[PDB]
Image 1: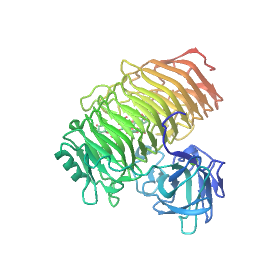
Image 2: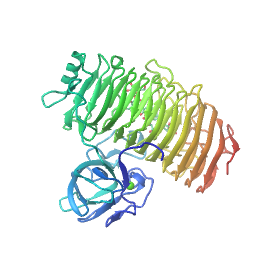
Image 3: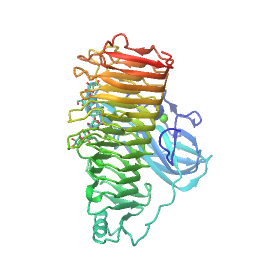
Image 4: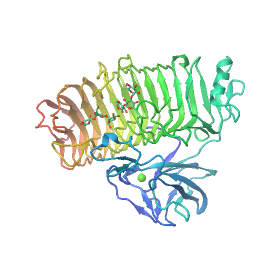
Amino acid sequence: GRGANMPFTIMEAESTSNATNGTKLTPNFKPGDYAGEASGRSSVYLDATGEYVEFTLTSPANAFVLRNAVAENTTGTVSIYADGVSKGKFNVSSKFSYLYATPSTLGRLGYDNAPGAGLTAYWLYEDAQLMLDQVYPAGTKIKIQKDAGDVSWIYVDLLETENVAPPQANPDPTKYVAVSASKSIDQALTEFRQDNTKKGIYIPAGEWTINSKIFLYGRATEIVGAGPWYTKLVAPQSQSNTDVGFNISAAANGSTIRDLSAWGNYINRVDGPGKFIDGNGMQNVTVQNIWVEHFVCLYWGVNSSYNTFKNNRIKNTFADGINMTNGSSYNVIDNNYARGTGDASFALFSATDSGGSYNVGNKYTNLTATNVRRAAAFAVYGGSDNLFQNLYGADTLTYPGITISSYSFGYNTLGFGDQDTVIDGATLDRTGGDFWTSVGADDKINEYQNFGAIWIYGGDRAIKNILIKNVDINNPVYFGLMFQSMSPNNMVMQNIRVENVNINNPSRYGIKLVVRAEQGQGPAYGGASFTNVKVNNPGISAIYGEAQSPNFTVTRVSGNNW
Ligand SMILES: OC[C@H]1O[C@H](O[C@@H]2[C@@H](O)[C@@H](O[C@@H]3[C@@H](O)[C@@H](O)O[C@H](CO)[C@H]3O)O[C@H](CO)[C@H]2O)[C@H](O)[C@@H](O)[C@@H]1O
Ligand SMILES: OC[C@H]1O[C@H](O[C@@H]2[C@@H](O)[C@@H](O[C@@H]3[C@@H](O)[C@@H](O)O[C@H](CO)[C@H]3O)O[C@H](CO)[C@H]2O)[C@H](O)[C@@H](O)[C@@H]1O
Ligand SMILES: [Ca+2]
């Protein structure tokens, strides 16, 4: 009931509703582990010819996405059956998975694709997409099976199913110049610009190369596809880390991109390039119903305002999904789905290194973000008057479900401003995790620093006016809520409120006031108010750190069972 409303249905392979003659992993929360990195922290291991997982369709489907893990540096197949009749072969491959690092060098996570001595493999799961020539009814038994000739072994994590409409044709051949076998995207855009009666271009079903950053200028431009399953923009797969996509300047304010998919060719993170859409001051641009993969980001906006991001799918990128800096204001990020982003899936960063003030007035609504391969599902870094509402986040590999931080990351930065940053209506399932190193740390349980479902981090910038309300935190890895001040700046927390929050079976505490994260770090400064904040069945205590935090005040307004 919370998050994005998407046309596809996700079914976990390990659900005991599904018959299998293979191996269900028992869950853990461990990076670089096939259960830890899986959706729902488990998957079904198919290991020998004839092993299968049998799903039952709850909704008709003609298209299927298998999130899976196969061996490093292999491509192959796994079989799919409909009611016991074999119907195709998924094309599975570890070409975009397996990024290498070390427990002590987790800052390199996402950047290094080559195996080497002493390196652990992370980011183990990738996706295979398959469309079948039949719409199958609900109640169909869809069997994922390892036949002779299929890959040696495979971890089956989940299957999304979708009933995909037929491809939409050119809305009007007189108003949209058509990409074709003889006409490239670039050429169609030239003809559009040069003929004032055209509203833009139509990209039809098929696979179209994008080896370029396509700049949209001149006037508001409409870029329309036949559907994400049918219109595929394809970065050249023979190459790697090719910066392609769209750049939308202010000349093309009011432009539209919709109903297509873009398949990148990145195999590791690169900082600078790699965004599918570049927003430099763009305004009133609508990005709608696109499906992006294997880019660094879907979108990175710079001082772009009044834009709409609606119904998109962001899967398997190497850094953020959607992020915005430099006074990017009054944008609507509504009804988007993210899975397997390589950094925070949905974020707002008030960086001012390009002459912009606060990110203000933005709305991040009906969002779903799972399997965050690094950092948080939702991250808010400074800003003012920004709303995060009706969110579902789950299975972060390393970090909180929600990060609220005034840390500059080394840039010219504004902290939180005069109006509340609000987080209203969130469900976070199995969020938090392990990252960085915990040398000299208090409350030390392992090699790493441990992160609660929600992290309130005072950095080197002001941290104030934060309202967290109507949040359900189910089985966090460690804590529900975690308050932490960076030393030595010791920025004081004012006007933090937590209302109607349930923390269900946190393994350690429901509330952790960080006392010494690291050598050189001290307790948190400021305070926070608590109303109807319920901690149910903690592992150790309901709240940790109160007595050791003399510079932090806990205001128990009412309703608190701790
Ligand atoms: O305005 C800051 C710069 O943004 C771009 O750089 C990004 C990098 O800084 C980095 O961003 C981090 C990001 O992933 C996020 O989750 O956490 C931090 C704060 O929210 C960010 O610092 O990596 C991103 C992906 O490669 C970069 O997009 C611009 O390219 C750069 O010119 C700006 O200076
Ligand atoms: O995955 C989180 C981000 O990683 C990178 O940014 C780093 C900062 O988050 C930060 O990390 C600190 C870490 O070194 C250790 O000291 O713990 C601190 C808190 O307990 C962390 O805040 O600082 C580093 C230097 O600026 C950054 O390397 C990526 O740049 C960013 O994209 C990620 O979102
Ligand atoms: Ca699973």
